[PDB]
Length: 230
Image (cartoon, rainbow, N blue to C red):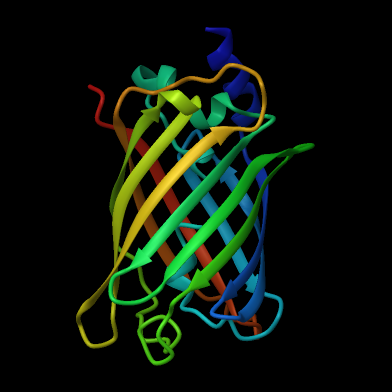
């Protein structure tokens, strides 16, 4: 299927990634740069994020979902349902509202596209209504991350997809801070895209630190595999 081919030839081996984020959460301004590489054959992303403006005013874990669904490993039987690679190289927009239960919300707007050989994720993030002393602005979340499944459905009237899912962030006391994610993606180009049957992506995420890095930063290893169409 030459539409499948177009995605395969773009994603074949290891593809460099650049991420750039501009953020304002309750008027705490910050910027994050990330670099690393994706290997869609294995659903594998390896990334290091640096807060280039100093101390990151929110917990690193709360930005993980915002910081590349095009690197998902779609099994062979599901390749006709991979919207994300089908929109490349021109790319897609990914927008979210992330509601932190009993606290504020993030609103994010991203553009994911090729710039030459490099796959780039340009993000603006606005956080409003956060509590001073709450789990987010008060840095009360643990530096770890749970596995979650993300359910993708077509958003046919918009030629794109929509996704709704819950992330549970462990709080330092043993409890959990729920982050309800609403998401919409639309292609940037005029070209056709693959609109998927309902299915999910299965995420595994591991957070670490560069022992040689003095800046405020996050090392992120993620594995992402499509499933749920047998």
